[PDB]
Every structure is written in structure tokens, then in C-alpha cells.
Amino acid sequence: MFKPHVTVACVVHAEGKFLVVEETINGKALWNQPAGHLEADETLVEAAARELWEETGISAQPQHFIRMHQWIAPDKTPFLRFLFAIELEQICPTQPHDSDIDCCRWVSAEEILQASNLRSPLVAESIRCYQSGQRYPLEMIGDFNWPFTK
Ligand SMILES: [Mn+2]
Ligand SMILES: [Mn+2]
Image 1: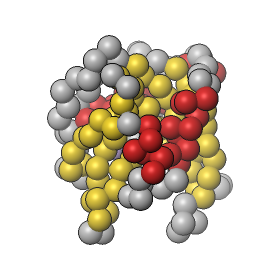
Image 2: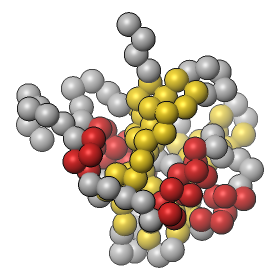
Image 3: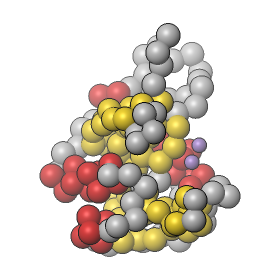
């Protein structure tokens, strides 16, 4: 049965900047949203909150649903990437709990769109969706008669 990879990602915004994670991937440092795979017996939204925590060490629940992109990666690996928005009042400290993460930067929209080191083109598209003002309720992609405790 064809299954596809399912990932979650978060636009995090505060004081006019966005949070970005810097991973080194074979020798170069790239930027992504905080993003991750969805794991088993997990809610998308739950998954987004864990990947945020793991990649940045921020405790925050995703606040809205921006959009989902379905795309294929350069090596033909298929994705359903669920994108979310969180707003905070101010830039908050960060501390990744994942080894693969080198660091977090808080950066302007135009730095992300001009940047030549993005992990994929969805990283800038993401900022383009955010900026369109598109958001939705979390309930758009929510769970149904979930067996486990939230
Ligand atoms: Mn991760
Ligand atoms: Mn992960």
C-alpha cells in the first residue's frame, strides 16, 4: 500500500521575525522551519508541538492551520507537509534538544525569501503562505474519536 511521508512544520512569528532551524546537511548549513515527521499514535497537531520542542526547545501549541503542500523531493520521496502558525509576543530563548540541529535564528521574511541555503523551496513558500494572511482553524485537519488522551 503506497503510503507517503507525512511531516509537520511551523511558522513561528514574533517581533517581526520568523524562527528558522539551521541543520548541516552534507557539509552545508541549511535553514528550515521547525519541522518533522509525524509519528505513530500521534495527532498532527501533537506532532507539530513535539517537533517544535525537539528542534528548538520551545513549549507552544500550534495556533492555526495555514495549509498543506503535497510535493515530491528531489530524490523522489513523497511528502504531505502540514504547515502551522504560532504567534508570540516576543522573541523567546531557544535551545534545541535534537542533535541534528546546529542552532535557531530569528529572521526576517525577506531574508528567508532571498536566502540561498534553504533545505527545500517549501521553506520560502511557507513564508509566502503566511504573508498572504491565510490561516484556518486547527479543526480543519483534526482527529476523530481519538483513542488516547490529549
Ligand atoms: Mn526533527
Ligand atoms: Mn523527528
